[PDB]
Image (cartoon, grey):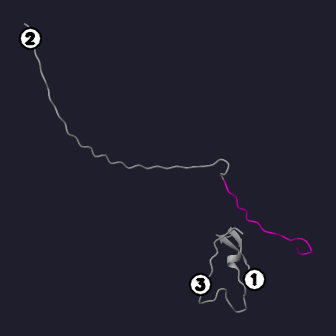
Amino acid sequence: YNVLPTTSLVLGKNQTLATIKAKENQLSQILAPNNYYPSKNLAPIALNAQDD
Amino acid sequence: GFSNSNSSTVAIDHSLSLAGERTWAETMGLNTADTARLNANIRYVNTGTAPI
C-alpha cells in the first residue's frame, strides 16, 4: 500500500540521466498481487517531474 | 574675336532597383558565473557489519 517506487533514467551502458522518487501524482494506493497499476485496459501513467 | 554664349539644359530621369539579400547570423551567449552544470554517477558501499 501507498506504492512509491524509486526509479532511474539511464542512457548508454551506465550513463544515468536521473534518479526520481515517485511523487504524489505517481502514488499507487493498492497494488494487489498479479495486478497492474493502472489496469491493463487503461493507459500507463506519466512521470515527468523532478521536484518534490 | 569676341564670342558670348548661353545654354540651358533641362533633364529628367526615372529609375528602378531590385535588391535581394540573404543574411546568415550566429550568436553564442554565455554567463561566466554559470558556465557548467554537474552530474555525478555514484554508488553506496557497505563494508561494515550492521545494516544502516
- Separation of marks 3 and 1 at Cα, in angstroms: 20 Å
Q: Position of residue B2 (x, y in %)?
A: 8, 8
Q: Secondary structure at mark 1?
A: loop
- In the image shown, does B39 or A20 lie closer to the viewer? A20
- Pointer 1 local density, CA inside 10 Å: few below 14, some 14–19, many at least 20: few
- Position of residue B41 in the picture relative to residue B4 (left or right): right
The Cα–Cα distance between marks 3 and 2, rounded to whole angstroms, is: 106 Å
Q: Tell me whether the residue at label 3 lies in contact with that at label 2, contact meaning CB atoms closer than 8 angstroms.
A: no
Q: Quadrant of residue A11?
A: bottom right
Label 3 chain ID: A
In the image, what residue type sits under mark 1?
A: Asn
- At horizontal 36% and vertical 48% (from top left) the residue drawn is B21
- Name which of mark 3 and mark 1 comes first in the sequence: 1
Q: Badges 3 and 1: C-beta atoms under 8 Å apart?
A: no
Principal secondary structure, stretch drawn in magenta? loop
Q: Give the residue drawn at x 61%, y 82%.
A: A44
* Quadrant of the drawing holding the N terminus of chain B: top left
Magenta part of the protein: which range? B36-52
Q: Which residue is mark 2?
A: B3
Which mark, by number, is residue A24? none
Q: Out of A3 and B20, give the one closest to the viewer.
A: A3
Residue matched to label 3 = A43
Q: Residues within 10 Å of mark 2 (few under 14, many from 20)?
A: few
Q: Nearer the viewer, mark 3 or mark 1?
A: 1
Q: Image point 66% across, 70% down: which residue? A: A49
Identify the amino acid type marked 3.
Ala
| Residue A12 higher or lower than A1, as above or below | above
Spatial CA span between label 2 and label 1: 117 Å
Q: Label 2 marks which chain's residue?
A: B
Secondary structure under badge 2? loop
